Amino acid sequence: SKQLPQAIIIGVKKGGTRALLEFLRVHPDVRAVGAEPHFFDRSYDKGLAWYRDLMPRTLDGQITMEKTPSYFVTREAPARISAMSKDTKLIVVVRDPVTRAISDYTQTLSKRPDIPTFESLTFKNRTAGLIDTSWSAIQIGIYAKHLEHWLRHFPIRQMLFVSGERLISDPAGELGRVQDFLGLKRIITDKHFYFNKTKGFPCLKKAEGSSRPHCLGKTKGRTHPEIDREVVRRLREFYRPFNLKFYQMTGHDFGWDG
Ligand SMILES: Nc1ncnc2c1ncn2[C@@H]1O[C@H](COP(=O)(O)O)[C@@H](OP(=O)(O)O)[C@H]1O
Ligand code: NA
Image (cartoon, rainbow, N blue to C red; front, side, top):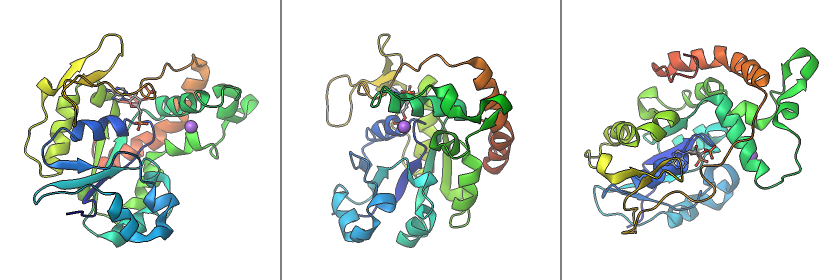
C-alpha cells in the first residue's frame, strides 16, 4: 500500500540530490518518487491525500522517499513536514557553497543563455565587494542560516548531512552512512558503481528498473563557466564564517575551508 514518506531529501539544490536518490533506489527496501513533488512548497494546498497518491506502493519494512531541493530553503517547510509527522528523517546533500552557486548559475545558463555574467550577479557593489545576499544562488549556500530554522522543529539526530564532494569520489562510502541513518542493511556497495571516463562521474552498473549501465542525464554533470578567481576568493571569504558555524552545528568539517 501507499505510505507517506518516512524520509525526505530536503536539500540542497545542486548538492547532488538526484544522484543520491537514484543510488538509494538500488536498495531493495527503498521506494521513491521519480520527479520532485514540490508538495510542501508549491502545492501544499492540495492536501496530504494528493501527496500520498504520488508515493509508490511499499511492502512492510520498505521505506518511502522523495527529494525536493527547495524544502531546505522554503520558509514554511520545517513546520509543515513536522506536522505530517514529528519523526520524519531528513537528509541534506550539501556541497561547497561557492561551487553550488556556480552550478546553480550554470543550470540557469542552460535555459536562458542571455543572462549577465556570474561576477556581475555576484555583487550589489563590485567596487566595494558587497555581495548580493538577496540573490537566491548566494542565499541557498548559507546552510547554517536555514539549518537553525529546521532545528526548531526537529532534533539534529533525525537530520543527516551528506558530503556532495565525497558522493562523487566515493559513492559507496557516503551511501554506507545513509543506509545506517535509515536503518537499512548495508547492501549498496562499490560493485554497484563504475566510473565513466567520458561522463566524469560515477555511474550505476544497474539502475533500479534497468539491467543496463545508467549514468545521469544531460542535466547532471554540466561544464561550469570560467569564473574570476578574485570573485571566488571574495565568495569563499563571505561563506567562511557561515561554513564554520555549519561545521559546529553538524559536528563535521566538510573540507570547504581546509
Ligand atoms: N554520479 C554523478 N553524476 C553526475 N552528477 C553528479 C553525480 N554525483 C553527484 N553529481 C552532482 O549533482 C549535481 C546536481 O545536483 P542536484 O541533482 O541536486 O541538482 C551536479 O552538479 P553539476 O552539474 O554542477 O556538476 C553534479 O555535480
Ligand atoms: Na538556477
